[PDB]
Image (cartoon, rainbow, N blue to C red):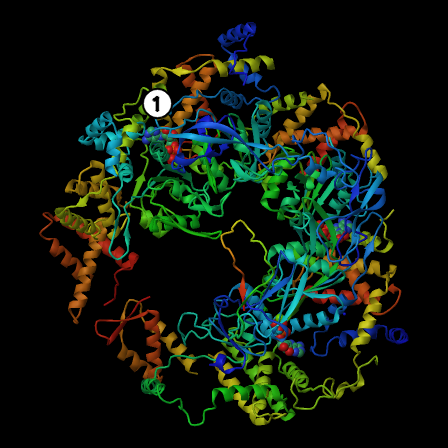
Amino acid sequence: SDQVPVGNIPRSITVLVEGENTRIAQPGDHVSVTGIFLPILRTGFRQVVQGLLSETYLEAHRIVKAASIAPEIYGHEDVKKALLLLLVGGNICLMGDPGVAKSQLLSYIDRLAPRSQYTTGRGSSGVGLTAAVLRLTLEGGALVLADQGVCCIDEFDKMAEADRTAIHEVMEQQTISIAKAGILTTLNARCSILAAANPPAALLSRFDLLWLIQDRPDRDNDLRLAQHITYVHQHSRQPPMKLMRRYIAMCREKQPMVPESLADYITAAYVEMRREAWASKDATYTSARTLLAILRLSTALARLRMVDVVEKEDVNEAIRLMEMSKD
Amino acid sequence: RIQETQAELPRGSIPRSLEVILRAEAVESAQAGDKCDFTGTLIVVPDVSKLSTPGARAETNSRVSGVDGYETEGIRGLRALGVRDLSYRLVFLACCVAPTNPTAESIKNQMTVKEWEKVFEMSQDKNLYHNLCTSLFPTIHGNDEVKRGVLLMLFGGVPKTTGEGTSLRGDINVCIVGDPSTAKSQFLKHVEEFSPRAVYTSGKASSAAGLTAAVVRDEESHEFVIEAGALMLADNGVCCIDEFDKMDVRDQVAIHEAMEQQTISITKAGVKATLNARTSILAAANPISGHYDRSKSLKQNINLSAPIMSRFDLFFILVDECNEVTDYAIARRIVDLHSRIEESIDRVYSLDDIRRYLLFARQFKPKISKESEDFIVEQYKHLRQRDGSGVTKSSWRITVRQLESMIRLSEAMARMHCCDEVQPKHVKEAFRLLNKSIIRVETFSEYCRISNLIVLHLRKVEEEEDESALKRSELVNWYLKEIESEIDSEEELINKKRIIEKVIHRLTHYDHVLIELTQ
Amino acid sequence: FVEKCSPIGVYTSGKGSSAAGLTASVMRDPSSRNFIMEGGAMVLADGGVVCIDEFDKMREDDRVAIHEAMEQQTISIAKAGITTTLNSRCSVLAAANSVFGRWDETKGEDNIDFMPTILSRFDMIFIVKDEHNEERDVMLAKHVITLHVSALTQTQAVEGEIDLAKLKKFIAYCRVKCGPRLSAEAAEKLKNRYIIMRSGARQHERDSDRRSSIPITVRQLEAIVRIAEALSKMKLQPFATEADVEEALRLFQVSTLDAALSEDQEMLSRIEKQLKRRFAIGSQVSEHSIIKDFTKQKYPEHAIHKVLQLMLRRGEIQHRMQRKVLYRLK
Amino acid sequence: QLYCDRYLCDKVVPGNRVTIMGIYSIKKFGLTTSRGRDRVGVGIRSSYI
Amino acid sequence: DEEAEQKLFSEKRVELLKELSRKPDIYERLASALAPSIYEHEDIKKGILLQLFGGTRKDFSHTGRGKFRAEINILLCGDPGTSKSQLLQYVYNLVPRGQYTSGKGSSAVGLTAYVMKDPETRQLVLQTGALVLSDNGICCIDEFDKMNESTRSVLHEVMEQQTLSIAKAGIICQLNARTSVLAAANPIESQWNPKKTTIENIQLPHTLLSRFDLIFLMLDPQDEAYDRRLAHHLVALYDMAVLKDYIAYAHSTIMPRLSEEASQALIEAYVDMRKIGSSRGMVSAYPRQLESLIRLAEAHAKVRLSNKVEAIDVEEAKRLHREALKQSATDPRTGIVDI
Amino acid sequence: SIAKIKKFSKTRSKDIFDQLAKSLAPSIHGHDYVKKAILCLLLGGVERDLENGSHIRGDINILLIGDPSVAKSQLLRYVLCTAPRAIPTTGRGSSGVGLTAAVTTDQETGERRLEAGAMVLADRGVVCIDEFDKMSDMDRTAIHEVMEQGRVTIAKAGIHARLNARCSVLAAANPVYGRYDQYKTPMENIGLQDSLLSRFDLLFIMLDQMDPEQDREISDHVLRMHRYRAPGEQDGDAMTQIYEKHDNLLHGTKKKKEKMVSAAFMKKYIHVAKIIKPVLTQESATYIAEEYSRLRSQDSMSSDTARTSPVTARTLETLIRLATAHAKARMSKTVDLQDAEEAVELVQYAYFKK
Ligand SMILES: Nc1ncnc2c1ncn2[C@@H]1O[C@H](COP(=O)(O)OP(=O)(O)O)[C@@H](O)[C@H]1O
Ligand SMILES: Nc1ncnc2c1ncn2[C@@H]1O[C@H](COP(=O)(O)OP(=O)(O)O)[C@@H](O)[C@H]1O
Ligand SMILES: Nc1ncnc2c1ncn2[C@@H]1O[C@H](COP(=O)(O)OP(=O)(O)O)[C@@H](O)[C@H]1O
Ligand SMILES: [Mg+2]
Ligand SMILES: [Mg+2]
Ligand SMILES: [Mg+2]
């Protein structure tokens, strides 16, 4: 999109790929190709101009494809920790008032992730999600492309109901099922979803973590935000990714395990938590899904520490994060 | 074209389609919609566009090579060696076509002596009216009115034409509306099983082109051929429509066109044609709320357009009783079906005998006797007088269409009993059935009667005199004076006085029917 | 008659016509990629007159487009890969019906459903009523029957009628030939009168304590200017005179101010307010008593009769067996 | 079907009511064979004015 | 395919299974062996097992009634924070000829069959959909609430007549769709609000609801013992062949039948159910529930490897029917579930 | 489709934007604030990019609400005539598909192709939306993507793209009650959600006050314009210096002491100013931040009047953008305090009403 002139549309080219170069690139990837530019003599329907016309194509010979998260945005440190945990791995939703930069966090997440997709609303609605048949081969949408990656969705509440049902299916079941005239398939989508929205029981019941961002007009916080924004606009750099990608890749290689003893402690905590939730009649949801989310967060933190056995600090930090999100 | 039947289908498989070819005399038979056995040969015929990839092919055995300037290249070499692609398809040639299971004089001659004996034995039985009800519907409990209506629709009336070029309907249409689980689809399924030419369709499953007809081009000649829809295959038969409310409004418009004109007009692909659709329609519909509302008329309980509503001859309404003893009587039958798979049935006539008798009976065209004219006139007069204000509101309102329906039902009864003329028994039966189909709205009558009497008195006072009028006390005294010959004691008199005073207060203040003025 | 008289004229109703819309539309031909535009009733006329019946029945899209069509005389349509601006220089002559079906004088406002925005674009507004005149009906009937009789023989109703062809050609000639502009002396008088009219309108709004449904804006001043210019053009003159502006202001008053100010109506409102309190619900009053009571107050009898007729139309008043005494209902 | 040559072009807009004086003729593009799956008509040349 | 052939040469296994069947607790053991990684919900697993066994496929063509549905359709209504989805996944992965649909993702034409033309040859007039491929199998429907009325119209005929009728241009046919349905549903508010009644919470037409054999109202009691057991099990998460052979043998070797005692027990159960369900607020009863009771009794008879249905089977079926709807705890005159 | 500019700018400084605002359109009477805002659109802000690929918007957006006959459409038409890339798109004239873009399957090849809408064609340009209130909700949700980031994301199975749509928007919408009600708060009259209001940089409310002297002035101006005739055309007929020559009627006898700028020089100067790239100074950053905090605290102090638009994080960017636009107006190298003061005056006027 950077190289397109003013008011025009991106142009396309066709590449042919040989033996070992085959199976290197996947749809949606950014690639650099070393190739030879050659024509093809065309024989077919008659044309206006006499002579020898041809079609061009490219023959390839080589194809080549805590830390600070979005340091430009001030505040939201706990949300940034939760985002780090979601990137590392073992579904996060943000609801906020307008004027708080929720879209920019999703943009940063899309840029950071190796496999990622970013959707803005009705522009990618329908066939942009799921998949469709084209001349026959089946081509997938954003959810299919982001398989084993992270997906980002903006203005979630404005989406059509069908898209929301598909998103719920992806979050819970992790596969898509399509049964329409001409299509009868099940698609694999092992991707984690980050969603943004404006101010429901569905989000609380289905999602794992919800972050509510309320703009309370405190003078000190607003003044510091103004100072940070002026610094950003003037010096074009925050006040004083490859390493982050390599660190995440090294981290995901390991898989910690839960010992037998700590279970009792965890069990106790869970019970007590639910008891408190039963004491506070204004509370809304506690279920085994919350315990599963806590276990997954603790395993992710243990993976961050590269420890073989889950430890106490990870469980405490997961409990604190869930408490902060709920409050 | 022929198709594999449903009974031969394996698991999860679409029926197989085959092409059959008729030569010379056998060409006549095997009309569309039949279910027939073929006897012949299985023969291989070449095809053209089967092989998108190269396959088996022919060539010549001569050891011939090319010469310079005439080298056997692609096209010239293939043409020189006479190479042909070996592609084939399977085609069936038929030499014998028979019905799988087999002009009144012709029908009589076709039947054997034993079949005619059985037909005559059936003919002179009054229990034919009763036993046919139980034979076709052994398992369904109760609802004998619906069984009688379905039988009358099956036998049908007589079509006629007038001297002005108009035509009069001879068919009967039936609709059933009921609460859930009142065996409503069982009647449709039983009629589909019994009838030889019947099509059962759901509301949303059948498309517009699925009904009516389609036009396609002939394979060899320049002419065109017509693919028959559900209504055309059910011509002079019965068409069953379940979930009648789910049909699209424009599909309902097409259905109403077929019901009124009894003709389908096609103007497509350079072909203009008119085809006959003399079908009788049996339809099932659900109430809007899923249950019948006893406090509202029929027009307020169903989402159907007025024209098609008026076209239907008979409407039947089924309501489930909550805790009557019938719950026992129903259960005894249902388990009897599960405990006794086939031994719990006491049919009087086999279905084939019934079909033969129906085929013989449909040929008759009875006339209308002289006394029947006056009897029908007086019965219609009584039916219309039933609509008077002296009784509660009814679901229907009676028009001339009810008179024509009565005539059609009389003709159907005469056809069923094979008599040569319409006689008062059939008229009485049709009158009885049409009255029993009508259901009165239940919410009151006494209040309405008192209000009407008061209105009549006040308006007579207003119209008869330009002088002064009376007051409330005068009205009460007048009504009591008129009742004086009807109340024997003071207690009843005072109770009725209190009741009428409260009723008058309600009329003046709540209903606003009567106006009150000061001195 | 306007449609026939004007050199270019289109007669339409609300929602367009049988097979022609009121505004233009744009489509793309899929086989051969061409941007096709369908002529509407407004685009088909340029410099002509568009007569519009049933102004109330218009659809939403046409209603929005007609705002620009009336104001800037252009329509703007944008679709995928195309943006176009079409010219529509039409004069508008519209007819409409009452909200209740017939006019109700005492109700004053709320008899017109149009919002003030669309009503602002009009230059002059006329209100016509079925006025009771016993001796005028005889003249109307005689005129109608005389027309019916004389239509068969001679088309010479008036001595000095301009022939339709001559009138058409003369109108075209005057429109094409020259164009006039105002004069400063008349301009200052027009300014003074316009300021006075605006002041009176504001005073009326403030005193009546209700927003006027037919406002007086700059567009009405330009409308008076345009009417004076048209009167000047009718005589081929390059500059108008005081008399033209005086006639224009007379017409503008008679139409617009009588429409917007809709003592007779206020006095009828006073009578209605008095009667509503005096009338006892569920009681009878003799018409003679009401007539005496209001004539002792020295109000005209015709106003009382009209108020009683309007109440009869609404249904609050009913006659007894003898029409001498009425009673009140709701 | 009508044939217009030289200055007669663009003198008529679709929708106009016209009176036309002309010569009744047939097209002449050689003795071509009939086409399509319908070949009933024999010796028929398309006509025009 | 293999059931229709005499390949039970393993007389050792036959004897072992026939001896196992005589043991009393085997029923519960089967409910225990159906899913090792699933929680204390034994009633749900028992219902799924009875679904697996299925009712007897009687022949009623001579009667003229038509086909009689011999299979079991089950519904699970509850909050999203439960394990119904895992149950559907396990049933899909366990049984051959299984299909899975979810909410609005499927259309009315996507099911049944649709018109096609071959990309390789000239024509292939009709192609089967999701339901027909599930013939003699299991179809698992999730997010049943979001499905439109157009697809529910198809489901109405599929769930009862076991057949489909298609009438389009040049295509008139009847197909077999002998499937068994496992449906999942959510409350309208995504919470089981106790102030609203059961019918108001579910928000489905009674015609659709009546055809389900069993309805499981998943509710959260917040018991401490439940919390401790589930937490311990879930954290601790950090013979199949014998079951397969037994299920195949029972499914392919025995035809259940019932005597007059079972008949009268069924009739008594039916009238009692009608008495209980008469009150408004709760799901009313219909005659199809009698057939559902018959099917469950026949499945339970199959479990015990018995050709004769005893009163024990009918009583167990009645117990399951009563417990699934939670009619015992539910207030009969207000339609509100209590604890 | 140099010395003069340098001398004029260096000599005038503040008088540059003063005269440009005053001489924007003689055909329109008064409304200095709206003329200033339109000039700010014409000059615009500065697009900025950083290391992480972050994008910061630099365009301005305005919404005008007023009584009928306040010449909003005249302003829109003038901006269409003057701006280089200007496209008019009314409320129901164009739908959501024709605004941004669409995807079509090419029958000739079977591929997927992109067709650009109104906003994509108007890259670095102006889109004018008359009768903005009649636009449907979904179209405004679609316009959100263009108004926030300036890009359009498009996707259908087989193709997906991010098209550039950096643009500025004018919009005019009628009040819900036909005429603006004085007593009711502006929130009831506007009838728009807070998110959409935050999307716009400026809100303006225009009223037709019937003051006799104001009406006299309006009548004088209108009739002076009406009586005017083009020089060189005979009466009664049918149908470059930096400063415009004085006219007896178009300007008046009193205005002889001042002059108006010619249109051609105005366009040349606007283009040159749009080219110039100013920079923000340290003096004004703290000043603007303190005033933003002052406004967000005054939120409690403004008790006698209501607020037209909510104050969010976008307000600070709007302040900086207006400051940079004013710095563009007078050719220089850095943003000064006077531009910040002018921006703050505009914000104070637009954001609150009596
Ligand atoms: N905490 C913050 N730090 C820096 N900039 C912010 C912050 N919050 C908001 N912003 C600015 O405000 C704007 C918010 O717009 P956007 O993120 O599109 O809102 P939303 O995502 O709610 O639609 C962004 O351009 C961003 O530069
Ligand atoms: N009166 C009855 N006699 C016998 N069986 C009945 C009766 N009423 C209902 N049933 C049984 O209940 C079921 C009713 O379902 P169905 O008729 O399909 O309902 P609907 O047609 O209203 O959708 C049938 O399977 C039938 O066996
Ligand atoms: N301030 C003003 N200066 C000059 N003319 C004006 C002014 N305000 C209104 N007008 C006149 O009033 C008319 C208003 O029409 P229009 O611009 O369509 O109003 P709106 O856009 O509010 O509907 C214009 O023709 C214009 O000549
Ligand atoms: Mg955003
Ligand atoms: Mg049914
Ligand atoms: Mg305007």
Q: Is residue F251 left or right of residue C280?
A: right
On the rendered image, what quadrant is the C terminus of chain A found in? top right
Q: How many numbered discs?
A: 1
Residue F240, placed above or below residue E126: below
Coordinates of residue A324 in the picture (x, y in percent): 70, 38
Q: Quadrant of residue A256?
A: top right
Q: Nearer the viewer, residue A216 or E33?
A: E33
> Is residue B482 among the parts visible in the rendering?
yes
> Is residue F310 among the parts visible in the rendering?
no
What subunit carries mark 1? B
Residue type at the position of mark 1:
Leu
The residue at label 1 has a CB less than 8 Å from ligand 2 = yes
Which residue carries the number 1 mark?
A: B337
For label 1, the SS is helix
Q: Residues within 10 Å of mark 1 (few under 14, many from 20)?
A: some
Picture residue at 73% right of the left edge, 20% below the top: A259
Picture residue at 27% right of the left edge, 55% below the top: B506
Q: Is residue A302 left or right of residue C125?
A: right
Coordinates of residue A43 in the picture (x, y in percent): 74, 48
Q: Nearer the viewer, residue B51 or B148?
A: B51
